[PDB]
Structures are given as structure tokens and as C-alpha cells.
Length: 481
Ligand SMILES: CCCOC(=O)c1ccc(O)cc1
Image (cartoon, rainbow, N blue to C red; front, side, top):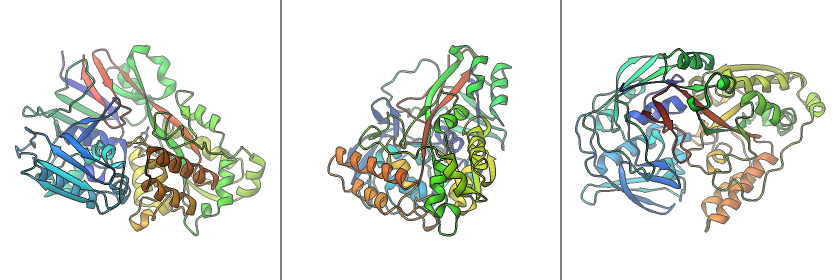
């Protein structure tokens, strides 16, 4: 009969919702701050917002009663509108356009009406879903006063969420303590067996072998496992959820090697999606030819992209002596094994390849902070909105360098146009038609290769559960049995 759960996870690159880029950022943001809506089967359930009304042009949220910060401040529309305003101006340009379709939403409170009104500068369907993501969590006025404070840990009175980070050992352990004065839980349709933990010790594991060993020796209760480690556990200690959707991102900027489309195609010709799946997921994942799974909106709509066939001969002629800075996330298979496979397939095509296999936190700083610092990566996307928009955004609009969402610096006139008619779309069908065509275009012009959807495998000790509701990625519901 304990009240403490010890969860394995990767090192955060920030504890501030505004600077969140990597899963560990969202995992911590999830405990400390409440979002307006939360994920569940068939869509989104009321969280800090009791209900909402609106289109893709504009949503109005009505804030719930009895909602309160870790200092006591009543959570009013002014607090919420201030938090979402602070987010829109302080967060990464990437995550802001992903949320509001742009950098300049209209956000306004009305403490009388009890409403918060958001008005995308152009219509944005992804807004409602985007506000279920941990990084949109409400920062109370204590947090807005000190943004440098939120990066590194708890600023007193900032938390809108059920926990406060009471103890910190940077890059080692983040100890979260449940607060006595919180009953503002979301309106979950789903019913969860077991007790909300009083104390959550978010424990940094350096690698998957370590993760497994510490479940098994009882240093951890819950932790992520690499597919090879499955056989070490009974089926009943495992909880398997579809997670990241993996696709290539090239540095396409004028002067870089993958500016030239003929180089991008050569990479496509050298990557066996079967071999890549075997090395990355060992068949626990699923191939996908788009920016999601079959559960992703529009992901089965026409057309299906025409992937480049393997041509290792044609790739050898093209990539001979070509210098490729391959950036790797260590989540892309055990210890970044998928990145290793990709390097190896480029090496045997005669490319001069240098792979940097880094932790998810370091990877995320590099991709979103210094986009010119690499040529190619396997991008493990977290499709938070459950649409194809997540992935299309990464290749269209203004560059990241110009405060856009365009990670790769790719200029696809077709894909850019199809992104815009997705916004002007009268019906869901036209929207899907636009989105599916945008992905097909991007695949045809060798702007990406869609790879797979991975499985997030939690291994857990007796007495401990963990649930992911409505295809959620950053809302791991820990329970003590
Ligand atoms: C896509 C944004 C950063 O990605 C992650 O933090 C991530 C993605 C997939 C995973 O399985 C783990 C982390």
C-alpha cells in the first residue's frame, strides 16, 4: 500500500510548457499544469474548460468553477487568456503555428461571461485538439512573472495542475507531490481502476537496457522497454500503445546537399522500409505511407502516395563522396538503431556520413533551435492533433528561420498551395482530399519518406497500471492498484 510511483523517462530539455519540444518536457508539463481539454475515446473531453462552442474559424471556451492555482488564485478567463497569450509569444514558432495556424491569434477573456474566446487569424481546425497538449497547460500569474524560472523547475503558485515538483536533481530525478487543494480533474468518459498517485518520482533512465533492469530489480515501477526486452517480462507487465509516426526530414536550404532533389531521391532509393522497421521496432510497429496511423484523420483518403522503389545502384552513382550530416534521436529504435541502419545504407552507397545519435532532448534543441546544423534526420513526430496537418506543416509555409513551421526549409509550390486549400475547405472530404494530395506531392518531390508508426512499450511491476486514452501521447495516466 504505497502512494509513490517511480516512472522511467528521458531527460527533459525544459520544465516550462512554453519551451516544451521533447516528450519528457510534455510528461512533466502534464503533471504541473492543466489544459482546457483532454483526450479520450471519440475525441476530446472537458478539462479546465467545462464546455466549448465554435468552428475552425473561432472557438469560445467557458472556464470551469472551483479551479485554482497552487497559491490559491481563482483560475479566471483573464488567467487562461494570459497563459495562452504568453504561450503564443514565448513558445517555439513551430508549436505556435501548429496550435493557432499562425503567430497572431486573437485571445480575450470575460470574467462576467466566464468565457475565453480564441480567433485564429485564419481558420484552423487543429486548434481544439492542440489545446489538449501538455505544453498549452495553464501557467498561473506566479509563472508569467518568471519564465526563466519555469525552465528549470517549480515557481511557487504557477501550477494549475494536480502536482508540484517538490524536489529536483537535474538530469536524474524529478519528484512530484499531489496537492491537497485540487479537485479539478477532467470529465473523463472512461473509468480508471486504481488510485491517483500522491508522489510521482520521474526518474531519468540513460538507455533501454537500464530501464528494463530497474523494473526487474525494483528500482522502477513503470518504464519504457525496447522491443528486444519484451521476452524478459510476462505479457501482463507490458502495456503497448501506438505512439510516434516516423518520417525523413531533409535540410533543403540553398547551399545544403539536399537542396538538390536528385540527392533526396538517392536517400529514398537506399532506405528499405522493411529493414528500417526490423531494426527500429522489430515488427512491434506498423509501416505507414503518410503522417500518421489508420486512426489519423484523412490517413485512408485518396490518393495513397507513390513511394520511390529501392535502387542501390542509382543511389551509389548519386551519393559517391556526398557529405551527409545525419542527426539521430535515440528513440528511433533502441539507442537510435534505426539511425544506425540509415547511416549504414548511405555508407554502402559511398556517401561520407557522420551520424550524431543523441537523446530526444538534445535532438529537439538541434532540430528546432539550429535547423542549419544537420542535413538529414529520421523525425519521430508526435501527431497530437491526430490529423495529417502535423506532418505537412513541417515542409510548408515560411522557414523556421523566418518564425514559420517549415523545419526542412523545403519549397514545394504544389504542397504550399494544397496546405492553403486545406484551410479554405468547405467540407471534411475536400479537407482530406487537400491533405492526402499534399502528402502525395511531398513524397513525389522527395521532401520526405514516410516510414512507420512505432509502439511505446511500458513494462510495469505488480500493483501499477498505466493507460493512454483516445490515442493520447503526453497524458500517461499512472495508477496504483
Ligand atoms: C516529435 C517531437 C519530439 O519527439 C519526441 O519527443 C518523441 C517522439 C517519439 C517517441 O517515441 C519519443 C519521443
